[PDB]
Image (cartoon, rainbow, N blue to C red; front, top):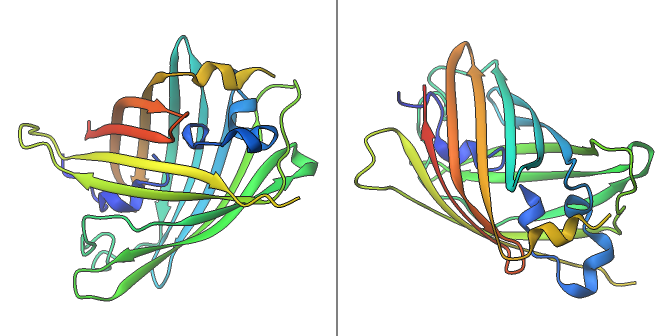
Length: 227
């Protein structure tokens, strides 16, 4: 079934443990340090002049697969707005996401705005508010302020009958001027993403399969509507 929302609005919700942390930043990689027990990732994504998504996700290893399992609830959207009206271009611009430590919760947080191109040449803003907390009790790495720089390309599989999104993404960490979970990310790691969604009461689900190569910061995934 056709997703009730544009695929680009789900990219940030659909595993920053696969970002490339260069060796000189190895003491600042919270996402890998939480593994294998993992972390909870919570967001509110507020679309300017429109509704909002609230998301809660569990990111962790299950056997040798890195899994990202999400519940998403969207409310107060306009049925003829850019999101429920499917008015967004099928692409996804570069971001620099500033990560800061959340010492009281033993985690990290981030606030950033995604710019979605609209088909008429305007832009739809999506304000992200993000909080990440480790699931385990063992120690994690609390980072200095830094950022993640992203690049994403979206494509279609001509032989896929279901509504879908093919995604390729490169992410590298930068910007510090001042557990053995990281060892699980050597080489290529298979990834499963599962999302259960409800936007304005329109129910849908997404499954993604692929792999991540954290040494180079590369994600390759195909997502299908399984509604």
